Length: 120
Length: 128
Image 1 (cartoon, rainbow over the protein chains, first blue to last red):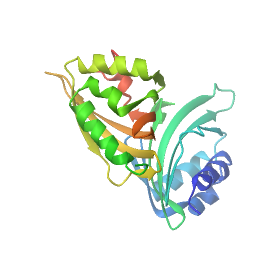
Image 2: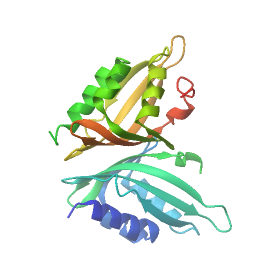
Image 3: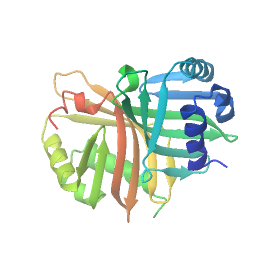
């Protein structure tokens, strides 16, 4: 159930597909995200992705297949997210993240990014 | 030994980093070690030279852990740590680090980490 494969599925079927209807499928209602010093609870997180998943943004994801760590109900890994906007130069961000699960859904993420997504 | 990685990481942070003891780099790190950190990639020799120069500086270190965020697996650990750096007469900087460490026979063989704010723009470290 909880595995690298499940975290990878969230990236592919929610982020890359920009499918806001799957936020609640992959994320626990008590989810909290920590990203580069910011903390967001589930509803802010969901409203934010749903607003972005409505724009003309596009996502591509690369995985570092050497960096995975898989424990019962927790995964850590290293990925690169490349973000494209209409006619704009694409930007690539490296993300290292820890995902802790509750009842098969993501309950906590702790992540940091380089260069920080704060101003991409 | 494969499930001891958290404890070895803690000891490295205490006996090598906070103590600024460059003699222990060869003890805690595999000779084939490679570090990936905020866009830098360093093999063992360059990593060891870089940290020798750090530890010869006036920097001081403090380490805290997020005990909720550990991930442990055979020969692997990921964690969330805060590294506070300071130099005399300078405001300290507290850097949040998410790191993944892979071990070979009790020695660190790979680290992948990203930090916020990036340590590479911290004045105490921008020399590195």
